């Protein structure tokens, strides 16, 4: 479709027919947005937010040019808010105000673009090593920045296989190593074992001064910190940088995120942001929610998302449907709906014969129960022909599959 | 400064002390934004917009993942609006629906990043040639993308010196040419002569298919089209791509822009956007304003911005102050205020001993008059010790300078 942009009539100042046409379009649009929001499950966006308190600020063009810390003569900005937000993220990952540098990004890809660019200026001859299941932005960065990339193999879970990382590293002891570590993969919600990655690096003869790690924690990077007894991402380990998405867990009307690296790394980048003009509203949104919820509030919500993910998985198994849920994940991978109009209604994310539900704060038991009824109901129709579902052990592991051959 | 993020008390659910604290902070903030907006002149942002009509849409997380044209399973998006906006920009630069590809960017730098990346995948061995006064994003892109860059010299106006481009091109006939053409330079509001650039290229033996041009029209790229008798940027010339900023002329609460290239070029890129998640509100804002104003409305406002720029220049000269205003520009370059707290109050953009006022739609004669009074008043104070204002001819040309030595040229 398209909604054309047509010239107003010569009469328009008298008749107001444009504003009237547009009002209906927007009304119609809004209605469809409301229902799409209601019935969304597939993507890692928290749809539950109230920024009514920021209502009176929405009409200014707030723009944080360049560095959050350097001042600029453009006065319509929100740097004090940005800095407060950054400080909070620094404290979260155990780096002191004076050691870190960071900024609020447009999105998850920008974070990956920034961290990887940093890695490259650290080690201009570095190879980029990354899981095959790391996000496409990682590989795009390699192409954009003209870097050799070595795609590491993956376990069933979607984790990086650190044994294949050994092979790769050893074969390239010649040159330094730039790593992309996934804190929650797009597809299976896998968490690369940071510690085993660091371990592998050292015992392949890469000392700290000869590698750089970016942690892409878009989704789960903000959730893991609040999981008790979970390997921490922290600048107390040889971590270069961490990206995380605002529009994912926090819930924002605009996409945004937070890139945090070390001060030392940013001087060796000698304006250190990928983008120039930066949406000064994003800092306000993040400032308001962090202030409102705290470590405490985030803890509650993470625990709930895990509980509800575990609920969804259990309930799928009981219904006969094979499903999987990694540790350190709110994302449930189950067998793809057959009629993929059901996929579009529920805005599910699909690949091969698998689909996933990312359980965010906005995803509620009521809404899961609604999904489950409508799934079971449409399952009967899809498979009334005596036809059976696909076997799923290829995708998810035999220990997780329920097909006739497995019930394992 | 900073506004700390502090944990709520254990009591907070009962007392609501956080929401109360924050309300004052936001109130205080808003008040300062109101006055900063009122008295802003230096930067190329139109501050005059009413998107009250879009008020009821502000609470959804609208996200146009990847390609405007490809569908995605995420249903909270605004692709139909984006496409409508793109079509409008395609028509503006004389390229048909089926020939062009484009998207709505986060900003001007993103457009430069995209167009230059396109140039590179066209000519992996290309040299990037760009004016010295092209925006720093152009040079960042070269570094990011590991490209040889040849900084071309500039005339006094701020235009690319096409004679120095000859020299540079001829010295590198071996390899193809990727050009960045400025439709309105950050500092002097110069317009690179696109035609003379194309001309120079051809008569240095670069046929089409051995060069790529990106037009960075961040500011003026949207204004020039509505200037009568102005060299057109159009896909009817050997143009690769054109970037333009929403938050500049149109006026937006969030930064955004429009990158438009050719379909052919994007297949040779084979997801073709720099960024992944894309703010789906930006398309709505652009859709609403384009629909509301049209070619007609844009014409009015451009003509007004020129008139008012010319007003400001005239008035500066009368007051004794040396100033310059290129044709094809709403940006007035005059002698930098001495006490640069006056600079911060008026949010002026400064470099060496020069400063500029970018006359956008929101910049009004009343507001210019206010600026001029307050300038003249503070000038007397700055210079009542027999100390003199700077000479400016280095920066702007002797034909534009009024200092004692130059009144007589
Ligand atoms: C979707 C995704 C991204 C990309 O982030 P955007 O906000 O879409 O730019 C990065 N990392 C992961 C793990 C993702 O799932
Ligand atoms: C400021 C500017 C840009 C950069 O655009 P952003 O919106 O700040 O990313 C590009 N080109 C010109 C001519 C500029 O003046
Ligand atoms: Zn099986
Ligand atoms: Zn002079």
Image (tube, coloured by chain):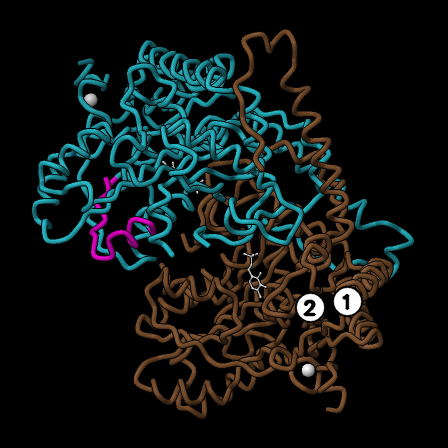
Chain colours: A cyan, B brown
Location of residue B216 by image quarter: bottom right
Pick the front one: A52 or A283: A283
Query: From the viewer's perspective, is B325 left or right of B190?
Result: right
Secondary element type, mark 2: loop
Q: Quadrant of the N terminus of chain B?
A: top right
- The residue shown at (72%, 72%) is B387
The relative height of residue A330 versus residue B192 in the rendered view (above or below) is: above
Q: Chain of mark 2?
A: B
Q: Residue furthest right?
A: A14
Q: Where does label 2 land, which residue?
A: B223
Whichever of callouts 1 and 2 sits on the residue coming sooner in the sequence is 2
Asked whether residue B68 is drawn in magenta, I would say: no
- Which percent across, then down, holds residue A399? 18, 18
Location of residue B58 by image quarter: top right
Pick the front one: B217 or A402: B217
Asked whether residue A122 is drawn in magenta, I would say: yes
Secondary element type, mark 1: helix
Q: CA distance from mark 1 to mark 2?
A: 9 Å
Q: Quadrant of the C terminus of chain B?
A: bottom right
The relative height of residue A221 versus residue B111 in the rendered view (above or below) is: above
Query: From the viewer's perspective, is B238 left or right of A49?
Result: left
- Which percent across, then down, holds residue A395? 23, 30
Is mark 1 in CB contact (under 8 Å) with mark 2?
yes
Location of residue A79 by image quarter: top right
Which mark, residue B305?
A: 1
- The residue shown at (69%, 78%) is B326
Q: Chain of mark 1?
A: B
Magenta span covers which residues? A117-132
The relative height of residue B311 versus residue A304 in the rendered view (above or below) is: below
Q: Quadrant of ligand 4?
A: bottom right
Callouts 1 and 2 in the same chain: yes
- Disc 1 crowd, CA 10 A, few/some/many (<14, 14-19, 20+): many
């Amino acid at each position: 479709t398209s909604l054309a942009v047509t010239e107003p009539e010569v009469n328009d100042e008298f008749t107001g027919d444009k504003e009237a046409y547009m009002a209906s379009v927007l009304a119609r649009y809004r209605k469809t947005l409301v229902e799409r929001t209601k019935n969304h499950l597939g993507y890692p966006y928290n749809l539950d937010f109230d920024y009514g308190a920021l209502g009176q600020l929405q009409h200014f063009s707030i723009n944080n040019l360049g560095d959050p810390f350097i001042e600029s003569n453009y006065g319509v900005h929100s740097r004090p808010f940005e800095v407060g937000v950054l400080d909070w993220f620094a404290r979260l990952w155990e780096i002191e105000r004076d050691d870190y540098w960071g900024y609020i990004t447009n999105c998850g890809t920008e974070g990956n673009l920034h961290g990887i660019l940093v890695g490259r200026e650290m080690f201009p001859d570095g190879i980029l090593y990354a899981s095959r299941e790391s996000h496409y932005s990682v590989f795009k960065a390699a192409r954009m920045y003209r870097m050799e990339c070595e795609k590491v193999d993956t376990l069933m879970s979607g984790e990086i296989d650190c044994d294949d990382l050994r092979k790769k590293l050893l074969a390239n002891k010649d040159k330094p190593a730039i790593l992309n570590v996934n804190i929650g993969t797009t597809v299976k919600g896998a968490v690369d074992d940071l510690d085993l990655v660091i371990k592998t690096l050292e015992e392949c003869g890469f000392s700290h001064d000869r590698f750089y790690i970016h942690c892409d924690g878009a989704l789960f990077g903000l959730m893991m910190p609040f999981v008790k007894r979970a390997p921490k991402v922290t600048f107390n380990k040889p971590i270069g940088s961490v990206s995380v998405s605002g529009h994912k867990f926090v819930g924002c009307p605009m996409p945004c995120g937070v890139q945090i690296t070390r001060m030392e790394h940013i001087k060796v980048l000698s304006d250190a942001t990928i983008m120039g003009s930066r949406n000064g509203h994003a800092p306000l949104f993040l400032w308001y929610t962090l202030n409102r919820k705290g470590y405490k509030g985030f803890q509650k919500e993470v625990q709930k998302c895990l509980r509800n993910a575990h609920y969804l998985k259990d309930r799928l198994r009981e219904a006969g449907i094979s499903a999987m849920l990694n540790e350190l994940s709110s994302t449930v991978v189950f067998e793809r709906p057959k009629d993929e109009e059901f996929v579009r209604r529920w805005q599910l994310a699909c690949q091969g014969d698998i689909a996933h539900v990312v359980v965010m704060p906005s995803v509620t038991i009521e809404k899961l129960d609604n999904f489950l009824k409508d799934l079971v109901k449409h399952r009967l129709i899809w498979y009334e022909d005596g036809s059976q579902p696909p076997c799923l052990a290829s995708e998810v592991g035999t220990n997780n599959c329920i097909c006739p051959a497995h019930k394992a």
